[PDB]
Length: 347
Image 1: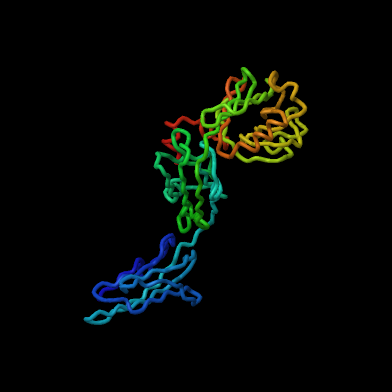
Image 2: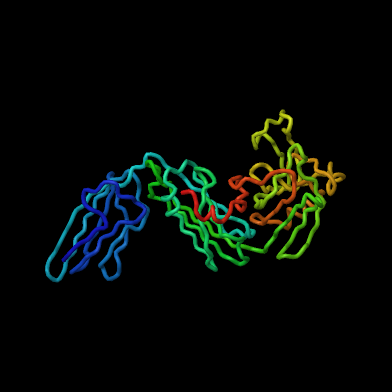
């Protein structure tokens, strides 16, 4: 009878991203036990036909295990002992995915994987991220910085699409001895198409649901001094009220363009600090003149309507302002990068 392990006796550097197995050939598996360096049994299952056995729980880094298996066929008996050592990472990194599990989002919500460390080997990271879509659509990876990678289609998601994201980084060398701290797996669905548009020509924020106008909001955006970049913004988090602090976006409150205001019904559409919010002090200007540092000022009535009917992932498109274009790597500006450049990636 012949025995076969998925590991070699004195091996060093056993990844641990996959389980350990043993197969019997011209016979059956009569006994299999794996134990770690400090003596505890690892736990595993033996298939019903008794031909294959595999560990059933997560194996650990910096571990020294030893396998003892015996196969006994009609002919005779065979036994082997193997002791190996798993990967001992130099450092550990944890990934966080967005959006949340079971969430329903807008058609512009990209898949997000953020590591709490810089990733030396992006290919290894990407390769370890499995994305399923239904109906299937072509998508690609692209890094916003050294820690966050994002995945999205060429055009906005088609409503009803299911997105499944499995980040199987546990046991994977993500570069320079950087190993995944664990796995994570979110799943979400794409809802109604909600595209709001802010035209600096009319200074109105038009909200379109499935191509139909359902709201027109007078608005005052950033003033010439500090305009609102034109472009496609992806709706992020929504707040019933929030103290906006310019220092959060790099501008000292005490500075000229600095500020700190407690506003209501605020929906964030830019990491640079742009929000669609209630601005009762400028309702006068709303619809006629820009007076903000960049945010889309709207009446308190419209900001709340916006908070109740807009979801993360929906889109806000700004056009014709005196500002430039929202940066592709902003954090919610993903759609401003040409598909051509995005699909090619930067791994």
